[PDB]
Length: 263
Ligand SMILES: CCCCCCO[C@@H]1O[C@H](CO)[C@H](O)[C@H](N)[C@H]1O[C@@H]1O[C@@H](C)[C@@H](O)[C@@H](O)[C@@H]1O
Ligand SMILES: [Hg+2]
Ligand SMILES: [Hg+2]
Ligand SMILES: [Hg+2]
Ligand SMILES: [Hg+2]
Image (cartoon, rainbow, N blue to C red):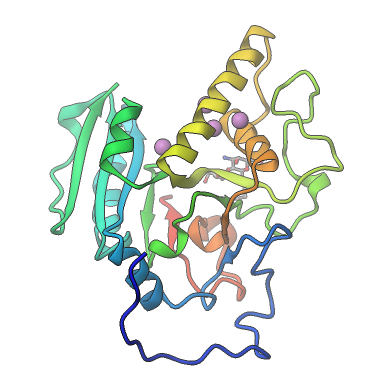
């Protein structure tokens, strides 16, 4: 809304692509976020001017409460640093949640296991798994009305290979000739409104399947892929945002491993 201040930085080169080894924009013109595609300084400016508040949700149940400490600490070093952050930890063990020191402007809410709440406390919801750790920068370059992340195991495969729900009896069914990408169920987000619409669409889809006595091959992840097929995300994060180094190594194509799994 408000204008940006004087800024000095490398002039974008029209005849010089940033990256030439990967697709940096989808067929529906949504950027695909890769290191080297964005100037964080510009993006930080734009989002700070709007005093943007990002909500980060995680569900730590049972033995998973153990990953909270590493998760929160690493997030404190790489997640939306400089912006307002609100962590929402949904757990079945409120007292097991570790006491993590948070930077200023960042807070944490423990929810023992409504929506209207999210609409008033944050501008964006980022939803991920807890058994993870941040290893590098994960910032506002990902914020958009709706985004999904490319699965680290199929980002170089053809649709026919994707592990979509192939049974026509499931609401998550996707034929072999349909599909843009295979998105990860453990890293998606967008505005509060768009994220609730997605989760509401999936919950209903999952009920219909249960009533029909069937469960999608990859559960939640199967429905997400179906919803994102019909509602193209406004931004797609590259595999840099969710990788398993132990299981997949470190390809030259990935200049950074931002969010990874904890062996
Ligand atoms: C992250 C490694 C990618 C390649 C392994 C296959 O990944 C699995 O893919 C299915 C869908 O086809 C599900 O998404 C599984 N959850 C994926 O497992 C992955 O690997 C295991 C070991 C865990 O790290 C899991 O979190 C990963 O998604
Ligand atoms: Hg969420
Ligand atoms: Hg869905
Ligand atoms: Hg769901
Ligand atoms: Hg979902």
